[PDB]
Amino acid sequence: WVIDPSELTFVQEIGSGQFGLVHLGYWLNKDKVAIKTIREGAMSEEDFIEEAEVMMKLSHPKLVQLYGVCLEQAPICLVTEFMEHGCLSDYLRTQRGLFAAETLLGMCLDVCEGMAYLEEACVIHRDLAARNCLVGENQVIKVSDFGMTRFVLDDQYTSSTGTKFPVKWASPEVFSFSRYSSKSDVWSFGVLMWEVFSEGKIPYENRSNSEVVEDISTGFRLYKPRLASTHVYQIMNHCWRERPEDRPAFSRLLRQLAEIAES
Ligand SMILES: */C(=C/C(=O)N(C)c1cc2c(cc1F)nc(Nc1ccccc1C)c1cncn12)CN(C)C
């Protein structure tokens, strides 16, 4: 799982993601790859390195595949499969008005399938959102960055009371207690479905973190996107049930959403 620096070449910078810059490149005797160069100070590197081998064993057609880590020299690099079309969030926003509702549902299903695999593996994403899903060939969506907030060194992001905490995607037991589970990922998935059917609109736009907490705690929920059917919106609302035990598992979501899609 360790990749030597001599085994990588960097071709072009493609953009910036969690923890630092990403390049298109090649990996010796292997493939074309994406390579993320971890910025100094952003990541708990030793903690991540301990987990990297087990993260690589996670492998599913709808999850971004970790291929290895280049760690001989600072800064360290993570290497993955290459996805051509960037973040799902940007992809929806830049092409707003073009997508059929069926295509939007299909994106949610791809995400749901990857999350079902994580659920079965007992791996919690912790920060699932359109902004960390990537878009590949034929508009396949793959889930990325699962578990990575365990290594983010910015306390304002990782603490529930932090000024940058991703409260818009957090279930009440996460925003209250940092009680993460696959059922808190299910809540996040409901907000992501909202993002997709809204073609990358910002959820709770111009609500402060404290306002989102208050709204959710007093029963407010995101409005139905025009492109979401009443049935799809019912499923979204299932993901935002207050009690995690009342939210469907991803395995159940996947069945429900498939039946809607295939009929
Ligand atoms: C989101 C996407 C984006 O615009 N780009 C260019 C992008 C592509 C990309 C990224 C990160 C990006 F910012 N990361 C990986 N793979 C990856 C994932 C996790 C850890 C390491 C690695 C290498 C990847 C694979 N194909 C394409 N990418 C940017 N937002 C607007 C912030």
Image: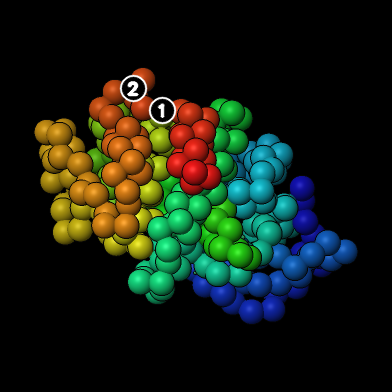
Residue found farthest to the top: 245
- According to the image, what is the colour scheme of the structure? rainbow
Is there any visible trace of residue 164 in the rendered image?
Answer: yes
Q: Residue at (59%, 28%) from the top-left corner?
A: 120
Residue found farthest to the front: 263
Residue located beneath label 2 in the image: 246
Q: Position of residue 78 (x, y in %)?
A: 65, 57
Looking at the image, residue 253 lies above or below residue 29: above
**C-alpha separation, residue under disc 2 versus residue under disc 1:** 7 Å
Element type at mark 1: loop
Q: Position of residue 194 (x, y in %)?
A: 33, 50
Looking at the image, residue 96 lies above or below residue 42: below
Which amino acid is tagged 1? Pro
User: Is label 1 within 8 A of ligand 1 (CB to nearest ligand atom)?
Assistant: no
Q: Position of residue 67 (x, y in %)?
A: 72, 53
Instruction: Tell which of 214 and 186 is nearer to you.
Output: 186
Which amino acid is tagged 2? Asp
Is there any visible trace of residue 236 in the rendered image?
Answer: no
Q: Characterize the local packing of mark 2: few (<14), some (14-19) or many (20 or more) Cα atoms within 10 angstroms.
A: few
Looking at the image, residue 194 lies above or below residue 259: below
**Image-based side of 205 in relation to 101, left or right:** left
Q: Position of residue 83 (x, y in %)?
A: 62, 64
Q: Characterize the local packing of mark 1: few (<14), some (14-19) or many (20 or more) Cα atoms within 10 angstroms.
A: many
**Image-based side of 52 in relation to 97, left or right:** right
Element type at mark 2: helix
Residue located beneath label 1 in the image: 248
User: Is label 2 within 8 A of ligand 1 (CB to nearest ligand atom)?
Assistant: no
**Image-based side of 10 in relation to 246, left or right:** right
Locate ligand 1 by image quadrant: bottom right
